[PDB]
Length: 105
Image 1 (cartoon, rainbow, N blue to C red):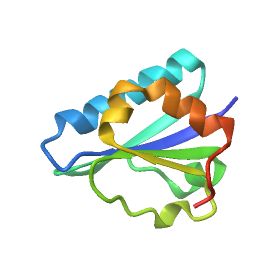
Image 2: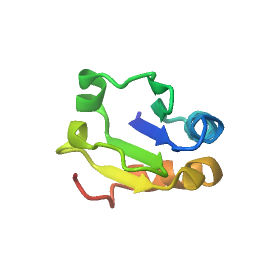
Image 3: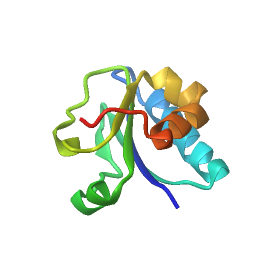
Image 4: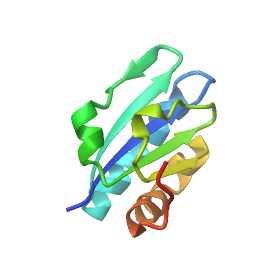
C-alpha cells in the first residue's frame, strides 16, 4: 500500500536524469509500491509533484548529482542519494525509504 515520490536530477544532459527516473519506476512496480517521479533536468522540471501527493507520500527519494531544493518536503521522511544510486540500486532505495529508518527533513 505504500506511496513514494522521487526527484531525479543530473546537471549533465538528460539521459541520466531519465534513466534514474525509469529505473525507480520499474523498481517500484516490481516491489508493488506506488511511485511518482519528478525530473529536474536542464530543460526544466517535468512530471511535477503536487502539494497533495507530497502530503500523502510515505517518503521522498531524491537521486541527484546537484543540490535539489527540499523546502516542499519539510516534515517528510527523505532519502537523498546520487543519480547513480537511482539508476543502479533503485530497489534498495525504495526498501530503505519504506523501512522508515530515514530522518524527517
